[PDB]
Amino acid sequence: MDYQEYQQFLARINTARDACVAKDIDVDLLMARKDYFGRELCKSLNIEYRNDVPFIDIILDIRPEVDPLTIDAPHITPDNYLYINNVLYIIDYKVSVSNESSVITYDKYYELTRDISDRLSIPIEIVIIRIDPVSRDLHINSDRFKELYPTIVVDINFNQFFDLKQLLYEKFGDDEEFLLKVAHGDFTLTAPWC
Image 1 (cartoon, rainbow, N blue to C red):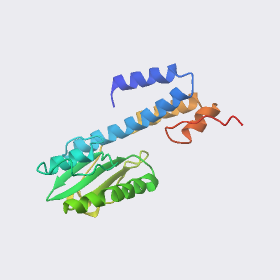
Image 2 (image 1 turned 90 degrees about the vertical axis):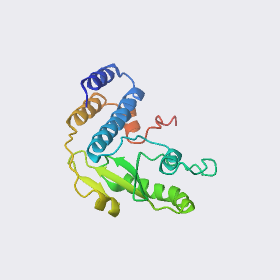
Image 3 (image 1 turned 60 degrees about the horizontal axis):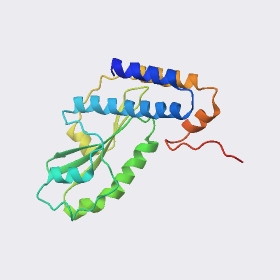
Image 4 (image 1 turned 135 degrees about the vertical axis):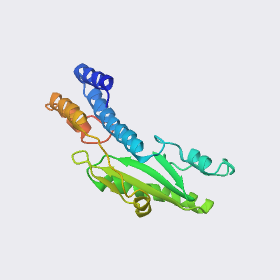
């Protein structure tokens, strides 16, 4: 965390009169909780910090001798990557308390990446790192990634984030439109006109 980000978030919550701004604060807080997790985990993973790096850039980095025009561009935007022993991990970061999104993202990545994996004839994998905000547990599905990194410890906390989220939710607790917005994703749709 940081003092300046705390100050600007507090000011944004106080400024909020509508529900669109409240939903924007909610989603930007949640992405901040994701960026902080990714930053700290990378700090502790001995790896470079990436953030939604394009897949074509990953292919260019691992093997720059290939033509970057014959390569198809998949819709995937991998969060981080890692190449070792002609083995490629598509690193992701999730702060979800359930595997409900984790498995969805893993299956989407598999579907979108197996074709390119087989056209280059090189072993690539997908790694999902799920952390519970309430308890800092690390969940990894990739067996080989677990073998690669069996000893990782994290020293983070989610007290500032929890407090700010609750302060926003108690400021807008009585609002119906805000609750209807936060019940779903970032594409906000107001109550029906009929």
